[PDB]
Image (cartoon, coloured by chain):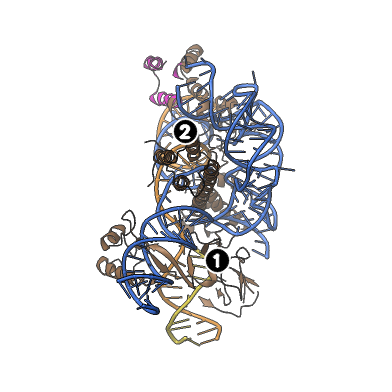
Chain colours: A brown, B blue, C orange, D yellow
Amino acid sequence: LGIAYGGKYTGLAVYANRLKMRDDVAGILKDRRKQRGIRRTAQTKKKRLRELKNYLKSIGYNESTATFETVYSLAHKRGYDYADMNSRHRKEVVKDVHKAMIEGRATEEQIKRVERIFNKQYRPKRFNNRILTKCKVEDCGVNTPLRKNVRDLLIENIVRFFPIEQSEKDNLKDAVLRREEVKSFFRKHKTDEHIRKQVYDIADNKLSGRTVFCKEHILEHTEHSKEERKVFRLAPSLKTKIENVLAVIKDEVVMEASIGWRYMRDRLREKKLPIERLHHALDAMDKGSRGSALHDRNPLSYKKGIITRRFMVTEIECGKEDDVISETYREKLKEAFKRFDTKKGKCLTDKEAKEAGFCIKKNELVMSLKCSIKGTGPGQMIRINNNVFKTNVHNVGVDYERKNPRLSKHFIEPPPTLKRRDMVTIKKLGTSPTIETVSATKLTKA
RNA sequence: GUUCGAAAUUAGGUGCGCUUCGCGUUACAGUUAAGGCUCUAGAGCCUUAAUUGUAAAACGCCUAUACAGUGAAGGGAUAUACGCUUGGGUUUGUCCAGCCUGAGCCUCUAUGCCAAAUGGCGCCUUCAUCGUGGGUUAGGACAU
DNA sequence: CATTTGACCCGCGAAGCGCACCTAATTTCGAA
DNA sequence: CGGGTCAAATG
Ligand SMILES: [Zn+2]
């Protein structure tokens, strides 16, 4: 093998071929997770609002009444409850709800049910039993316990090696799980400081995670010492990296980033391969995919042929203020940059915007300016519900460009067989695709 | 006695999943503040910006045998499910991740909250009732 | 009038829970 | 952070 991997690169120094691994999948999953969290928060907000509306209408506070107005507006921003006394606390929102429903002449049971709606848990929190480490011995596929549920077994695993009799071992085990008793025992039955910490840690600490062995095998681990450490749960991004490297190996070991070492070591054997744990070889993405974003995350405004969007003054770049629609605020922003000298950093800053007089919002917060969107065109605009989005995956091929079947019903501009990366006699696609900085129209299939 | 292997423990980092709280975006509607034009100091319209409210945030796919509210009763560690067995939806060229989830079950895993036993509560179940919902999707491989 | 050709575009923050998989170190037991 | 966008410019 000779594989050696590190940082963003790897080398199969059997051969001396270097390979570049994907160093993005982690950040892509991170934002595929932030998006899912945003979506689920919004769905729970809709659930809660539906329930609150139904209840308020059921008790005579119909939508036209001020009680409904106030309570429904309060239910949009209910505050946080992870702690107790950028957001208000659940208690302040519920205090305002009580105030409004009292002023509405509501009964105690009604206010209490509205409070229950404001405190309801719409999606269960399930985290106590999610990741399931199975027992290491080959004949025991059963679940290992959480280490906090078998503190007795873990304490026994340590006390079974003390120079004392079994009766004193059992007494000590029962005492530590009787506080000064264990201290006196150790003070008399001199024991190593590390062993004493370990037993105290098992007795007292918050034991996250599971044990390598089940109940029936925690103590028997010495009988299985020759079996190496096993792995079952590796990060999908590291899995993608390592499996791309392994696929390269399959098409075509002192393996010196260290995470996931055992997963490679086990895939390299797939039975007994030994392991000895830009010039890297000398030391030794497809955004059109079916799971990529169909469009941008921030919707755009598309009015009478002009694409614009609101960007904060601290989000509009120096040298680009010409996209700001307002003539007056363009001049104001230019008057701000010939004092700020922001051309280097180009980002501008909250303090600078406030000093320049762009703090116009409710909380003295920096205003926003509508700016025209460069780098986009009409062909990329889609409309879903009220939102207009830029889609970078509008092109799936060219026959005249071919529109994305997942967006044909949403394109604002009506439409008038080389796919991307095909071999022809393609890095960017269109009616005259870019083929490799040369662009041509008369490509032919090859 | 060195080395190596395992387990345990601790700290760091990396990452994965769940549940929320916001800001920002967008659509409409109402206001305020200006800028302009147009009718005639006002009045009508367009712009920008602020402030209010409500609504959308991937497309889709799958579910009404579904889903949630309310009430009653029963069960609640001889119990349930995030567990086990075995699925199904997302799901498509195909296969997956991840999430969700049905039926049976308690051999492994887990089991919360408010008040020493015990007591409520969440929880599970059946029914009655008003109904209109719920899950997943912004990732990876392969083929094309 | 098809090509270069050069600049431009792209959602952020926090909290509460779980978890694994690698480093660093120690104990203990097994071996080779 | 590729896949485009526009307008410009041997054209
Ligand atoms: Zn076992």
Q: Under tag 1, what secondary structure? A: strand
Dot 1 surroundings within 10 Å: few (below 14), some, or many (20 or more)? many
The answer for which chain carries disc 2 is: A
Location of residue A310 (image quadrant): bottom left
Upstream in the sequence, badge 2 or badge 1? Answer: 2
Q: Which residue is mark 1?
A: A382
Q: Residue A32 in the image: x percent, y percent?
A: 52, 53
Q: Chain of mark 1?
A: A
Question: Residue A349 appears at what percent x and percent y?
Answer: 31, 59
In magenta, the rendered stretch is A175-203
Which residue is labeled 2 in the image? Answer: A108
Q: CA distance from mark 2 to mark 1?
A: 49 Å
Q: Residues within 10 Å of mark 2 (few under 14, many from 20)?
A: few
Asked if residue B17 lies left or right of residue A203, the reply is right
Q: Is residue B130 left or right of residue A146?
A: right
Look at the image and say whether residue A331 sits in the magenta stretch: no
